Image (spheres, coloured by chain):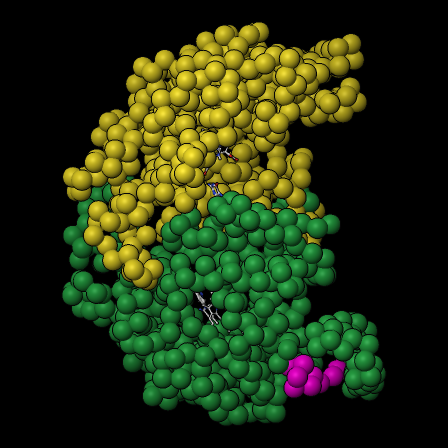
Chain colours: A yellow, B green
Amino acid sequence: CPRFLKVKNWETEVVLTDTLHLKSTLETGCTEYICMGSIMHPDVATKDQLFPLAKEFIDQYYSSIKRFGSKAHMERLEEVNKEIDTTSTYQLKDTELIYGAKHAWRNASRCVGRIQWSKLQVFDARDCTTAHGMFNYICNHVKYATNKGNLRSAITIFPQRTDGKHDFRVWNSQLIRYAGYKQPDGSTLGDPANVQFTEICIQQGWKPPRGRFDVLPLLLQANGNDPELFQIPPELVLEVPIRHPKFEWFKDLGLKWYGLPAVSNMLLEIGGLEFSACPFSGWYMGTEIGVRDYCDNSRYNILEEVAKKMNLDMRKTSSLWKDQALVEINIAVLYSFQSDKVTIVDHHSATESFIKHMENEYRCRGGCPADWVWIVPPMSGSITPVFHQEMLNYRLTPSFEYQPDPWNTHVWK
Amino acid sequence: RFLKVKNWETEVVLTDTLHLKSTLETGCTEYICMGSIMHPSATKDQLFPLAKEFIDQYYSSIKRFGSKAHMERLEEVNKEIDTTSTYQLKDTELIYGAKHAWRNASRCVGRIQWSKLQVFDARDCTTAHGMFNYICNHVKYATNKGNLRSAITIFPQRTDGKHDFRVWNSQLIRYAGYKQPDGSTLGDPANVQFTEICIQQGWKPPRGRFDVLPLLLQANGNDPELFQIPPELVLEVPIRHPKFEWFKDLGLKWYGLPAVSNMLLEIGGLEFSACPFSGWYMGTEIGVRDYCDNSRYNILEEVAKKMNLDMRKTSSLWKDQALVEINIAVLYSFQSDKVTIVDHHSATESFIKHMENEYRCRGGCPADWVWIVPPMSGSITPVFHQEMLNYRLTPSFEYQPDPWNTHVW
Ligand code: HEM
Ligand code: HEM
Ligand SMILES: Cc1cc(N)nc(CCc2cc(CCCN(C)C)cc(C(F)(F)F)c2)c1
Ligand SMILES: Cc1cc(N)nc(CCc2cc(CCCN(C)C)cc(C(F)(F)F)c2)c1
Ligand SMILES: C[C@H](O)[C@H](O)[C@H]1CNc2nc(N)[nH]c(=O)c2N1
Ligand SMILES: C[C@H](O)[C@H](O)[C@H]1CNc2nc(N)[nH]c(=O)c2N1
Ligand SMILES: [Zn+2]
C-alpha cells in the first residue's frame, strides 16, 4: 500500500494526509474489484495466534505512555509471554484495560461521537461470576452514566472469553429498550425491532405489560450458564416525554424515549483478548431517535400520523410532506431533551465536532478511520460538513466488533 | 463468489453474479475502503483485447455469439487496429455502447431509463462550428418544450491525444460566477474559474446572478471558440413557492436541462473525450446542492430569515426547515411550468425497482450508495436501507482532467 493517502474536503478544499491506515489489522471486506462500503456486516485464539496479537498491543500501550523499549516494557512483554505459554491466555493490567477500551472507541469508524473518546469511565467487572453480579454492575453503570440527566460516557467490562463455553453475554442489544409485541392480526405493538428478543423474554418467564413503551428486562448470562432475567429498577431509567415547542397537539401522540443509549451486544477485542460482554453508553444524537427510531417504516413509523396532524397534503410525494413532518419530529425530540436537561446533541453540532476531531487526529495520530455511510446523518446530509468530507475506512485494534446473537449459539443446560 | 445484498427495511435479499464480469479497479483494498473518495487513485496491443471484449458482449447481447457476423466483426476490427492504430464502431455498436455506459454508471440514480437514450452520432464533426451545430440540435431535441428527453451527442474519438475534441464547459447550460472587489461571489461560485476563461477569451459578461455562460468548444485539438446558445433554446424556470408568496421575490431561477459535458465515454478501448449527455433533474440537485451548499448559491440564511425562523441555535433545525421549503418550491415550480423533474422519493423508489430488474435479468447492478442516497431525508427513502455493491463495468463514463490544465495554445 502507498504510504501517504490524501483525503479532501470538497467544501473547504482542505486536504489531509493519512499514514495511520498502514497500521490496519483486520479486513474491510472490499477488494480491488468490488467495494462493500454500504454492506452492514461484511473455538478461541491458540497460543501461537495470541503471542503476536498481545505483543502488538503491549508495544502500542507502552508507546503511548512514552516508555517504549523501557525495562517495564520488556518486563511486561516477558510476563505476558510466560502467561500465554503456561495458561494459553493472559490478563490485562487495569491501566491496559482502560487504554484498550478508550482506543476501541477512538478506533470505531462508525461512531460520530469520538471527540469524547478519552473521557470514558471504565468499570472493571472482571471479578464478576454470576448473573446477579452482572446485574449489580449494570445497575451501577446505568446510575453513573445517567447522572440525573447529565449523561457521562461509560463502559463496564465483564470477564474475557476463555474456552468459548463460559462466555459472559448481555442478551439485550441495548441495556434500555422498548418491547415489541406481534399481534394475531399481524400488527405490532411497541417497537418492531425488538419482537424477537421480547418473545425470548416472555418464554424465559417475563410477564409483559403489553404497552407501547415497556422497558425490557435484562437477560444476563454469566460463565456460559443459562441466562437469567432481571428488572431494571424503574427509578434508574430516565425517560423523556416528547413535546413540540409550537405544536401543542404533539404531546397527545403520547411519545417518549429513554435518555441512555447503551449498546450491550458488541465484542471488545484487546490484544487478542475477547470481552464478549462490555456494555457501553454515551448520549444520543437527536436523529437516532427522531429519524430512525420514530420514522423508519420498520420501527415506530409515525410520519403519517404526524403529517395528518400537520394538515399536510399527503397525496403527492412531491409535496415533500414526509420531509416536512420529519423535521418537526426532530425539532420536538431536541426540544424535549433540552427542556428536561437530559444531554443530547443535534446532528449539526455533532458533525461539526466530528470534523474538528478528525482534523486533530490527522494531526496528532496520522489519520482517523471513518465510515462515511454511517457518519453522515440520516436527514439533511449535505448541509452537515461530513457529507463533503472524504473519509478512509479501515479497522484498527483494539476494536468493538459484532458477534452472533447469543440465542443462536447458546448450549442450553 | 456469489454476493448477497440485503434491504434492511424489506428484508429482500438479492444475489450478485455480475460483479464477476468486472476487470477495472475500484481503489479499495482488503484493508482500506475508499468508498467516499470522489476520484480514487492506448496502443494496438492494449486495444484489441478491449475491442474483443466489447464486440463479444455486443454479440452476446443480440444472441448471435459465435455467429458469422460476430466472427467477421472480430476479424474486421483486428485488421483495422493493425493497419490504422485504432478502429471505428458501427452505428449499432455506438448506440449499444452509450446506453450501456449509462446502465453501468454506479453513481446514477436515474438508470431505470437507461435504454431510452437518444444517441446522436457526431463522429463526422471537424470544427468548433460543427460542434456548436450538433450541440444546439441536442439541446433543442432534449428540451422538447419542457417534456425532457434523454440524449447524448458523441464527437470523434481520441486519436493521438493532441487532437482531442472537448467541450470546455462542465455542463452545456450553467450560470456564470463572478469574484467581487469585496471578496464575495456573484452568481455561481462553482463556475468562477470557467467564467474568467470566457471573459479572457472575449465574452462580455452581463454580471448578473444567472447569466447563461457561452459554450467554449475545442475541435480536433485546436484553441477553443466561444458561442452563445440561442436563448429560445434555453428553458428556465422561475422558482416560486406554493404558499410563501414572498418566495418569488428572492429572484431565483434555474435551467430545465441538466447536461453533463465534461466526461469521457469509453467503449471498447476507444475514448470519446466529448460526449455531452442530458436527462432531467432530480429536485434535490437544484434545491439542496446548487442552492444550499456553502460553496454554491448558499441561500439558506436568506430563506430562513423570510420564514422568521429562530437562527441563534443550530438545535432549532432552522437550516433543515428552510431546506425542505426550498425543495418544495423547486418541485412546484418545474411542475407548474410543465418541465420534467422527479422528486427524490419517486426517483429512489424507481431505483430500487430498477435494481430488482437488473438482478433478475443481468445478475447484478453496480451502485454507489454514497452517490445514490439523496443529500436530504436520506433514511426516509428506500435506497438508504438498500445494501449496494459498487464495481466498475465497461463501457463507462469516466472523469478526465479539465482541458485548461492540459491545453497548449
Ligand atoms: C458520547 C456520545 C456518543 C455519541 C453522540 C455517539 C454517536 C453515535 C452514533 C450516532 C452512532 C451511529 C448509531 C446508529 O445509527 O446505529 C454511533 C455508533 C457507534 N458508537 Fe458512538 N456515540 C457516543 C458514544 C459512544 C461510546 C461511549 C462508545 C464506546 C465506548 C461508542 C462506540 C460506538 C460504536 C462501536 C458504534 C457503531 C455501532 C454499530 O456498528 O452498531 N459510541 N455512535
Ligand atoms: C434521465 C434522468 C436522469 C436522472 C433523474 C439522473 C439523476 C442523477 C443524479 C441525481 C446524479 C448524481 C448527480 C450529482 O450529485 O452530481 C447522477 C449522476 C450521473 N448520471 Fe444520471 N440522471 C439522469 C440521466 C442520465 C443520463 C442520460 C446519463 C448518461 C447517458 C447519466 C449518467 C450519469 C453519470 C455518468 C453520473 C455520475 C456523474 C459523476 O460521477 O460526476 N444520467 N444522475
Ligand atoms: C453509545 C452510543 C451512543 C449513541 N448516541 N448511539 C449509539 C448507537 C445505539 C443504537 C443502536 C441501534 C440498534 C437497534 C436496532 N437493532 C437491534 C435492530 C439503533 C440506533 C438508532 F436506531 F440509530 F437510533 C442506535 C451508541
Ligand atoms: C444527465 C444528468 C441528469 C441529472 N439529473 N443530473 C446530472 C448531474 C448534474 C450535476 C452536476 C454537478 C457538477 C457541478 C458542481 N461542480 C462543478 C462543483 C452537480 C450536481 C449537483 F447538483 F450537485 F447534484 C448535478 C446529470
Ligand atoms: C444499507 C446501509 O448500509 C444501511 O442502511 C446503513 C446506512 N447508514 C447507516 N448509518 C447509521 N448511522 N446507522 C445505520 O443503521 C445505517 N444503516
Ligand atoms: C466526500 C463525498 O464522497 C462527496 O461529498 C460526495 C458525497 N455524496 C455525493 N452524492 C452525490 N449524488 N453527489 C455528490 O457530489 C456527492 N458528493
Ligand atoms: Zn470499499
Foreground pick, B390 / A407: A407
Taking the image in four quarters, ligand 3 sits in the one at top left
Q: Which residues are magenta?
A: B86-94
> Is A97 rendered above or below residue B176?
above
What residue appears at the point 63 percent right and 17 percent down from the top-left corner?
A412
State the residue lying farthest toward the front.
A184
What residue appears at the point 36 percent right and 80 percent down from the top-left corner?
B146
> Is A10 rendered above or below residue B89?
above
Foreground pick, B324 / B15: B15
Find residue A266 and report its horizontal and vertical position in percent: 55, 27
Task: Say which quadrant the C terminus of chain B sits in.
Answer: bottom right
> Is A300 rendered above or below residue B375?
above
> Is B96 rendered above or below residue B28?
below
What residue appears at the point 52 percent right and 13 percent down from the top-left corner?
A228
Give the left or right position of residue B200, taking residue B395 as reference.
Answer: left
Find residue B107 and report its horizontal and vertical position in percent: 53, 61
Give the left or right position of residue B17, taking residue B218 as reference.
Answer: right
Quarter of the image where one finds residue A26: top right
What residue appears at the point 40 percent right and 21 percent down from the top-left corner?
A208
Task: Tell whether position B90 is magenta.
Answer: yes
Please indicate, yes or no, whether residue B276 appears anywhere in the rendered image: no
Task: Tell whether position A183 is magenta.
Answer: no
Please indicate, yes or no, whether residue B367 appears anywhere in the rendered image: yes
Foreground pick, B369 / A177: A177
Find residue B320 and report its horizontal and vertical position in percent: 30, 50
Give the left or right position of residue B150, taking residue B341 as reference.
Answer: right
Quarter of the image where one finds residue B101: bottom right
